[PDB]
Image (cartoon, rainbow, N blue to C red):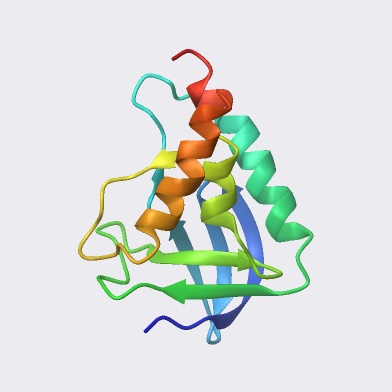
Length: 132
């Protein structure tokens, strides 16, 4: 039931937040279903540079809201973000720069897709998975 909508980069903020123009208005988006291990908060800069590269170099940015709540308690839009068709959320997890997060308010459409990416980063012992 999900659909991709057009958006335009304003600023890459960090690993999992980007400011976009969406339907004429600037808003901050938090990437769905990705977060950082408690007390392995490194890879912060690496995750920021990775997301920054990905969005800044994209011809096309798309927002895809899930079926649950569209904004978090901080007022950030909650979405899957695509750079020239490649999902940023998935790429961060695939690189071992983020783990899959707990589901927030019904936003679980790509949870198994992201779990598959995470399994492979873990098998390869990448970044957050380097210590066992």
